[PDB]
Amino acid sequence: KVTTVVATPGQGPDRPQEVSYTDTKVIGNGSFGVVYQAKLCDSGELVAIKKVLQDKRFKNRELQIMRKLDHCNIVRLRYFFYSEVYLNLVLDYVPETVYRVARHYSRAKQTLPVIYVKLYMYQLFRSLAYIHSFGICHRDIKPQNLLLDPDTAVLKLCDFGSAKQLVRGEPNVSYICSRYYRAPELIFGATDYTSSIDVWSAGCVLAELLLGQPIFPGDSGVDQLVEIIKVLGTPTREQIREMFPQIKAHPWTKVFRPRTPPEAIALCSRLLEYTPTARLTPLEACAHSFFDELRDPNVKLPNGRDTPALFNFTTQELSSNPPLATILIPPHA
Ligand SMILES: COc1nc(-c2ccnc(NC(=O)C3CC3)c2)ncc1C(N)=O
């Protein structure tokens, strides 16, 4: 019925408090453990609780990363507590994901309206700009990790179980990231990759939202590679070095359906690039013309509501390229 724990607030100083929740139901199982949904007794607010076995030999990386994140497009750590000992992350509950929503449209043989593609992708790139400004790479960007509130069109990035700060010259494991969304340098087993792998994944999500299906499917690395090559063409010797069947590149305009906005395709082509340093940074993507509509003072949601927070950039968020502020923050913001 009612569970009462002593939990430490996610943000702010380490001062624990009694927190009572109820209506606990399971909403997900995984390699990490279990995600519950519960209701806070004090406020009626819905939370997700992610339960993981605690390393005991060290501090939990996910927890350390989440306690220092504060951004409106990243799911909020409200509390954490301990309960073989387990670490429980209490997060704001979000009712949907890009995965289930994309699933709804594909099953109905429709595509998600481009206005939602713009809103969702833009917010994803902001969450990335934010975590990348700390040197933190998410390393598992995929539709199941993109939470959505369909009423307000707010997107929140979740799951920082793979996230890690990438320091130049330090090797990192290549076996991160989920099939379909893996950068080609990961497939090739590179251990010197950069945060731009997040950008490649984000481009895969964009292409999927436009196509109604994954752009580079395959149950093996070789199949994925074959699909990437069918689109990008055969990588050059130099492109390979930066990260085989000789195939000529398929014109990007012929990859998507006829009614697809050319700005959407141009954005795709600048995200999905062999050479990791040639991909757009998240902040640059935010500033891409594909998102200009979002910066239009007259824009509204299909449901009639105002757009959610889009322009509340901080100095930290802009730090990779401060003069983009002039594009990113429109006159009416
Ligand atoms: C399913 O895995 C996860 N799920 C969440 C989460 C957080 C807040 N709201 C939701 N909401 C939903 O799942 C609704 C049902 C679609 C999920 N957070 C982290 C993880 C993780 N694996 O780290």
Image (spheres, helix red, strand yellow):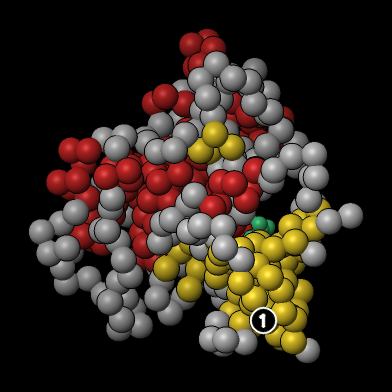
Q: Cβ of disc 1 within 8 Å of ligand 1?
A: no
Q: Position of residue 306 (x, y in %)?
A: 28, 77
Which quadrant of the figure has residue 325?
top left
Q: Position of residue 36 (x, y in %)?
A: 72, 71
Residue at image coords 28%, 50% = 314
Quadrant of the frame with the C terminus? bottom left
Quadrant of the frame with the N terminus? bottom right
* 13 lies left or right of 182: left
* 88 lies left or right of 295: right
Between 91 and 323, the residue placed more toward the observer is 91
Ligand 1 shown in quarter = bottom right
Q: Position of residue 12 (x, y in %)?
A: 48, 59
* 316 lies left or right of 55: left
Q: Is residue 165 visible?
A: yes
Tell which residue pokes out farthest to the front in this image.
15
Q: Secondary structure at mark 1?
A: strand
Residue at image coords 59%, 19% = 170
Q: Residues within 10 Å of mark 1 (few under 14, many from 20)?
A: some
Q: How many marks?
A: 1
102, above or below 247, in the image: below
Q: Name the residue carrying label 1.
A: 20
Between 230 and 49, the residue placed more toward the observer is 49
Between 19 and 237, the residue placed more toward the observer is 19
Residue at image coords 80%, 64% = 83
89, above or below 238, in the image: below
Which quadrant of the figure has residue 284?
top left
Q: Is residue 274 visible?
A: no
Q: Position of residue 91 (x, y in %)?
A: 59, 66
The amino acid sitting under disc 1 is Ser
Residue at image coords 69%, 43% = 59
Tell which residue pokes out farthest to the left in this image.
331
